[PDB]
Image (cartoon, coloured by chain):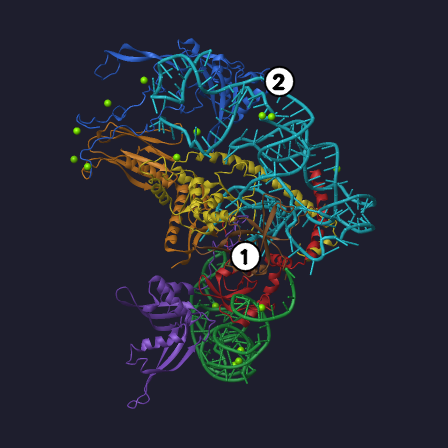
Chain colours: A blue, B red, C brown, D orange, E yellow, F purple, G cyan, H green
Amino acid sequence: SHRKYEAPRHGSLAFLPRKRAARHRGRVKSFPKDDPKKPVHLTAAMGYKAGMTTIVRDLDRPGAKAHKKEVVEAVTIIDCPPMVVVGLVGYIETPRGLRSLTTVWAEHLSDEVKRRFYKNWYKSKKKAFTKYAKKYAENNGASITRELERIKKYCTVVRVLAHTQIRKTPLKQKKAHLMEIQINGGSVADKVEFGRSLFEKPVTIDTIFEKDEMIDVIAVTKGHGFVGVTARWGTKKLPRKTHK
Amino acid sequence: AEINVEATSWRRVEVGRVLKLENGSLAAIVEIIDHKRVLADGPSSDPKLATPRGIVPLSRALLTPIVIPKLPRGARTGAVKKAWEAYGVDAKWKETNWAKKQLQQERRQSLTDFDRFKVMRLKKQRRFEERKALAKIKAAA
Amino acid sequence: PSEAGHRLYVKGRHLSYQRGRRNTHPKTSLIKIEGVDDTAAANFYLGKRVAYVYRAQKEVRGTKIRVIWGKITRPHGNSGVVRAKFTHPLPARSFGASVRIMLYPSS
Amino acid sequence: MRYIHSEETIPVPENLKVSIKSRLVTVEGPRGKLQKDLSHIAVNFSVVKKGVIGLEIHHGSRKDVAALRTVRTIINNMIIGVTKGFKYKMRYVYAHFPINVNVEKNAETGCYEVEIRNFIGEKIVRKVVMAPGVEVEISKAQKDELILSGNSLEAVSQSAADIQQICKVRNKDIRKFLDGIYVSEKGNIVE
Amino acid sequence: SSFESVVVIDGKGHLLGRLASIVAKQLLSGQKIVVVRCEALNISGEFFRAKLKYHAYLRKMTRYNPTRGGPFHFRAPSRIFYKAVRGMIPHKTARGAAALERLKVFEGVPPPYDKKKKMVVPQALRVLRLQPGRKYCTVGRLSHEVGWKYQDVVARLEERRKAKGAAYYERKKLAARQLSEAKKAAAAKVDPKVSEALAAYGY
Amino acid sequence: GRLQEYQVIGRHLPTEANPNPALYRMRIFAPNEVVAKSRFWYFLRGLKKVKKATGEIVSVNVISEKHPLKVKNFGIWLRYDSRSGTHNMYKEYRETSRVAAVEAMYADMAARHRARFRSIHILKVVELEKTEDVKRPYIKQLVAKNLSFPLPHRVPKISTKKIFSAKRPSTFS
RNA sequence: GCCAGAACGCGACGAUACUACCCGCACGUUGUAGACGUAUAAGAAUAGGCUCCGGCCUCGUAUCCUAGCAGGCGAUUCCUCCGCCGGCCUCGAAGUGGCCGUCGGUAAUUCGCGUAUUGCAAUUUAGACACGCGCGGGAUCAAAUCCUUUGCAGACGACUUAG
RNA sequence: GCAUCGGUUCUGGCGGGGGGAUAAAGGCCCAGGGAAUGUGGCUCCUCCGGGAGUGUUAUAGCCCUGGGUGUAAUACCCUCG
Ligand SMILES: [Mg+2]
Ligand SMILES: [Mg+2]
Ligand SMILES: [Mg+2]
Ligand SMILES: [Mg+2]
Ligand SMILES: [Mg+2]
Ligand SMILES: [Mg+2]
Ligand SMILES: [Mg+2]
Ligand SMILES: [Mg+2]
Ligand SMILES: [Mg+2]
Ligand SMILES: [Mg+2]
Ligand SMILES: [Mg+2]
Ligand SMILES: [Mg+2]
Ligand SMILES: [Mg+2]
Ligand SMILES: [Mg+2]
Ligand SMILES: [Mg+2]
């Protein structure tokens, strides 16, 4: 027989697979649509979360009830030491999707980035990019400039490899974090020239973002061990005299 | 106001049009029954091209470019034969491209093994002088 | 010099057994002959001999390849497929393999 | 019942040129050029005489024969449009609230668009953009007239129908509220 | 009939089910098939009928768990053709699986399979089967309104490979000029009797 | 099926009261004379009080076309059974022989009206002598002066065993 | 837009000790849904096309290649075709082809020696892909887990860190 | 494996005979009678291809009845090898 009284379902099926995230660092899935009429610019950053605090300001919203009156709002503070660019990548379009064909690195790598490629760094020999480094200063880097010309010839989107300077934070961790940030600009030649000019140099957050701008935040939520249906989905509790 | 139209144009089926049946036979149209069947016959001295009088379906026929002029509708075998000989249909058909290719084809199914070897050697003999001229022209460019 | 090949047989394929819709009889096989379309043309190969050659693992008497011998029995259908009978039924895993058709009993 | 032979003819005046290729018609004359694609109909074109175009269908059904006169009239309309053009007239009808329009000029491209304000005393500003090749004028001959003109009948008529269809009254008795914009006259530019 | 090592079929202008029946028979016989330009096939009937048929296909799914056992609805034109072929093969047996291993399907013309001769099956061509005046659609378009995402990539790329083929055509046309002029110059000069000797043999 | 014309003559068995009875003759279209006699007894049972047990067959013959190489128009009068009630028609055909018109009529009624062989009676078949006595417009169209028509879009014949053609065919025969 | 990511779907890069890797040829225990000339690239229309601008088109029933101990040894003849390497250009959908040069082979014509005996048939043991081995040349001198620790994590495994 | 035979069976080709309106048609010849989707002429219009009318073989031909060449050939059915 039918249900007696109607009610909406508990929870949402959009966020359905409720398993632990595959990777600790948050993953960006899409980037803003490219437009070749603005100057070249980056489209992402990454930092660490400090805490929350309270502010006070007055509102400017004509026709509202609290117009031209003081309000109290809560805010959050994100630590953002400068990041360092290490290399860039190019992708091509195939009838099966996007795929990367080349990548170029900088001459010198920090010990922070070099820590990322190892699981036991203390007892290793730290030979990460030793043989790769000799590709510089050999035929004046003809091999290196060859793939850069290839990217200028065959690629359609260009991303840049950047990492954080975690040593300037009170964190105990010494392993840095690495990601790619897409460059939206006029042309592929301009993109590659601008990206290459940023090798082993720091970039500050004020060049990327600016005041009163509407942004997005990606991270991994707080974890709880293993919970029942009442807290996981939010169902009604059974009467007090229920057995089992 | 000159107007130029380039559109296809088929071959008309009138009385006097000669068809080519599947087994290498020619027949002249004397009467149309439907859009699928016609009445035709061909009196020819050559026994290979001759056909009796009767009805032939239009799906088993091909339209040849030859047309007999001023053939009366529903004529008898004697009058059709008279116009066939006066117009010389058999002599006209011999020089068409269909007949020549058919003859060069027919000569090919009748080849003894010894003749196959002979034609292979003759083809190589002509090819030798063929490549010399090709190389001479290609070098000159 | 003399780069030509060495072939004195007609190649064929092993299609299936003789069957109804749910029952099969391994006694006779069906073979598709190269270049034959009608059953009148298929009459030329009646009584000829066919061979099926395959590779084994061991060497027994100077070779590692075995052969099974058979012969053509009668035409089948209107499309030139033919029936054949071998001393042993074919391994039933060769549905799609190739066989050699000789020209021994000539004319 | 299949009809063996059905044929029609179109005369052509000594002013314009016409060329057809792969059932694609190109008509060009003193007032411009037009294109039409007729690859979806099986018709046989031919030149009957020095100034007559013939078209025909062989072994067609009743349904197939029906489209022959449609094709003939479409090409004749193209000839008329390329030698005399077209011109439509429309009128505004309001009872209490006057309706104001603004046909601003080319918006950095060939298309015109007409803006309509104060329909039945509504504060919506409503915008419609017409297909290229149509020229819009506010008449000065007499009061409260809109003039549409162009080369192709299909585009001129479609733009006029867009104007007619955009002014609609909702949730009211339309036998009483006769407010709106309607078409009133069809004709050629010349004579 | 003839036995080739592998044969490549150009898919443009072929009826889906009529081509799939020939292919399914050849695979079970032992031939190797490669189908190219799967986005240019045709289906008889008006387009909306095909769309409604696909929607009725899309509504089917396992109730208790959609991640297992349920009919998985592939969205590419080549996968639609593959489903059609798979329905005509006993794919639940070892023999059927081996037969299916002899088939390749692609959209467009991949680089291994261009610079090759492309065959045509005349028992499935649309221009020889359908009535003029009837209605048909395109599998590529049907996939567009069901979720295929790479329509424009193949469309732009095909213009590139067709531009390369125009230059290859120009070279082939020039080459014929030397072969024809050489044959005309050579045949007259030398052979006294091989000409008519070949002519009597039909060459 | 494959028909041909017969004539069959029957008679009531002579008796002492009525020696020399009358003789009846009919024209019957039948594949063979075995069913020609059966149709003769079937039609006669609806006209006279004679059965097969009390009658006899005098003669059966075959009628052949006089001029089977001349094109002519025919007209057929017939009755049949529908799913409810009976009806009469009158149709026309154009061909070279009398027998084929009956063959075409049987196939035509079987296609257009779903009428089987069991429920068709042939009343009269007549050759149209003139050209102005043709009524139906699908036969009027075939006797126009200087008839001629093209044959567009005709598929060439290709052997059903030769798969994998090497070039695109053409329909310009 | 958003969530999971095929545990038998794919791509780029880093470092690779143990002949683990690369190059050359040497055989062959061993594997294969099944070589035996495994020879052929325009696009587009089908109620219209191709082109040498003279013509041509139902048809691949086509074109190329095709002789010699399973293909020997010499000569008269002939400047064709085929192959391995090397150097310059080119090719990104799953990266390919062209030109030039050295070397080796070569009936388009016509000849001289040799073939037997496998005994009147018995697959014509011959192809290319992998893989295991043996030599002789080059390059290289790495990581992971257990363990102690951390709490952004946690039923136990697992996860983020440090040594 | 081959040659010569026996039993059962499948599948090709060749030489004859009989029957029906002693096939019907058809070719050539003789005699008579007709018509039109009217041949050649003649008249008119159109120069723009041609169209309209009159009228029975002429510079094309067709239909109906009787006779010869005939015991003609061929199709279908049956039958001896
Ligand atoms: Mg309930
Ligand atoms: Mg906790
Ligand atoms: Mg709650
Ligand atoms: Mg209790
Ligand atoms: Mg109301
Ligand atoms: Mg699963
Ligand atoms: Mg995975
Ligand atoms: Mg080792
Ligand atoms: Mg070792
Ligand atoms: Mg040399
Ligand atoms: Mg015997
Ligand atoms: Mg006889
Ligand atoms: Mg006259
Ligand atoms: Mg007689
Ligand atoms: Mg006789």
Q: Amino acid at mark 1?
A: Ala
Ligand 7 image position (quadrant): top left
- Give the percent coordinates (x, y) of residue G144: 48, 20
**Quarter of the image where the N terminus of chain A is located:** top left
**Quarter of the image where the C terminus of chain A is located:** top left
Q: Secondary structure at mark 2?
A: helix
Query: Which disc is residue C84 wearing?
Result: 1
Nearest to the observer: residue E73 or residue C83: C83
- Give the percent coordinates (x, y) of residue H63: 46, 75
Relative side of D77 to E30, left or right: left
Query: Which disc is residue E93 wearing?
Result: none
Snapshot quadrant of residue C21:
bottom left
Relative side of H31 to D176, left or right: right
Q: Secondary structure at mark 1?
A: strand
Rate crowding at label 1 as few (under 14), some (14 to 19) or many (20 or more) other CA atoms within 10 Å.
Answer: many
Using the rendered image of the protein, determine whether residue E114 is visible from the camera's viewpoint.
Answer: yes
- Give the percent coordinates (x, y) of residue B67: 54, 62
Using the rendered image of the protein, determine whether residue E12 is visible from the camera's viewpoint.
Answer: no
- Give the percent coordinates (x, y) of residue B36: 45, 61
Snapshot quadrant of residue G40:
top right
Rate crowding at label 2 as few (under 14), some (14 to 19) or many (20 or more) other CA atoms within 10 Å.
Answer: few
- Are discs 1 and 2 located on one and the same chain? no
The alpha-carbon separation of the residues under discs 1 and 2 comes to 72 Å
> In the image, is residue E197 above or below residue G9?
below
Query: Which chain is home to disc 2?
Result: A
Query: Which disc is residue A139 wearing?
Result: 2
